Image 1 (spheres, rainbow over the protein chains, first blue to last red):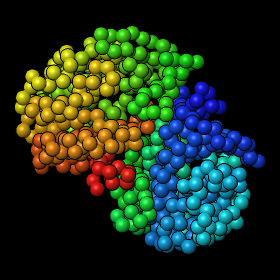
Image 2: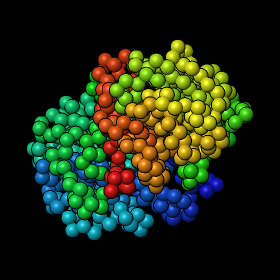
Image 3: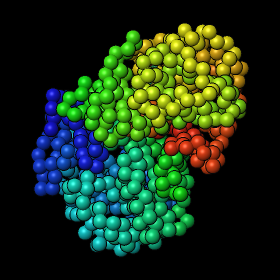
Image 4: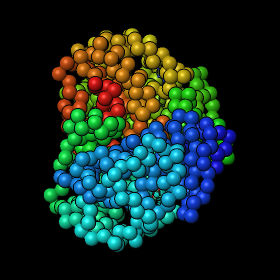
Length: 286
Length: 286
Ligand SMILES: CSC[C@H]1O[C@@H](n2cnc3c(N)ncnc32)[C@H](O)[C@@H]1O
Ligand SMILES: CSC[C@H]1O[C@@H](n2cnc3c(N)ncnc32)[C@H](O)[C@@H]1O
């Protein structure tokens, strides 16, 4: 687990490579009903949450992912008022969504209440979202939860743990049809979407699938040192055929960026996040 | 060190974090006059070159670095004819440079001819650069070599090993003044420029330093899984006060990108590479 002061992350989904983070102190290590939960204070990345041996987040760099997954869809919708977050037990996405004054209601469906309690203790800067008055906190499997909803949400965001745990249910491609049903007529979604350096083939397959459900599908990415290969992508889908994901319909002003305390996201970054290395552009377009 | 089938990279310049690569086969491990040279066949990244314990390149991902470092300055010059590469023992940057019909000669000054011999054996897709009729290969410390030149080059690229071992001489800020003198009146340069997630303070210092030497200075970055934190930046300097580094003065058509066999670089990627996360935009501009 932790050997000789280092925690090393290995996974069949990124074979032959591994990030290690040096450990100052072990903070928490218990199995919930659903998963193995491990938290440590790392030497240089602040606190680090691990679910079934895969890094969920670190306090040092969590802001890239949290801001981009929230603001990519939110700033691609002209007036999002009702938002659904699936997963996000650390509170971080919620933290970012509630910053938008157009957002009145955020329903969060998280399967594992233990994650929520440990994030409250050990990820205080992420879990600050739990004190928003916009929050409706829900419990359960997000896949089956999605079935409950029709024509209900302006924006849905899925921030999942790994396909080996409780998050497997969310990997049934039918979840995207459930999400489409749950969305209002002109709704948008953003899902965690594969690393283009690691599973370009799955992105191409997922894009093609999404394309036959939605008039507008796009792939974007951001960098984050502590994700495998140092970055991750997002699938964006709109039921609105006029959605242009690459040009934000709500461009943030610098004053807005400042007020929101954003450390990664802005309008230019929104645009560039869609510009892919040639190999990936070719794969997904040609 | 390889231990239990893994190579693990640590460096005080990225404290508390490590990349490990799984080793299929040790291939070469010898000290030259200048440095320790380690080559292995990795399980999932092809052949890997390590100098004094720091990864220089992997066959699987080397292309992002090689292509960006060459095309960022070359596509920002209206007619680059005379090129200087400092370092580049693996032949990778050379490979990318000679693709340009405008280039008539490339001088490459490499300190360590054993890196050249190991790369020609173990990095054959990179060492294909050495085949070029445009090459004038030179031996020595690129620092002292820089002093020999005045008003000689359109473009200078410095692709060095790390600020331990023989690349120390190139980390003297004076080297930038030497490159300015070595450049033609409208010459441009590209140097490896620091990871914005690791040493943003250093980029700020370096940009201020370069701005007092050159009328136009820019910072861009590319992603590369096997660099610390998954990415690296580039300092771009022009002696031409009309240079706009962010908009390529030489745009490439799709046909050209196809012809050049590019896997990462293209013109949209060029422009996007100058779009920094908010925290680094703030630090470098505000
Ligand atoms: C920490 S962010 C990722 C979160 O997604 C949660 N999660 C995983 N699977 C599901 C699911 N099927 N439904 C709702 N939330 C989930 C995990 O418990 C974790 O908190
Ligand atoms: C493998 S690419 C990086 C290269 O830079 C070379 N290099 C390091 N220091 C110097 C120097 N002072 N002058 C020229 N080349 C150098 C290294 O030997 C290596 O081949």
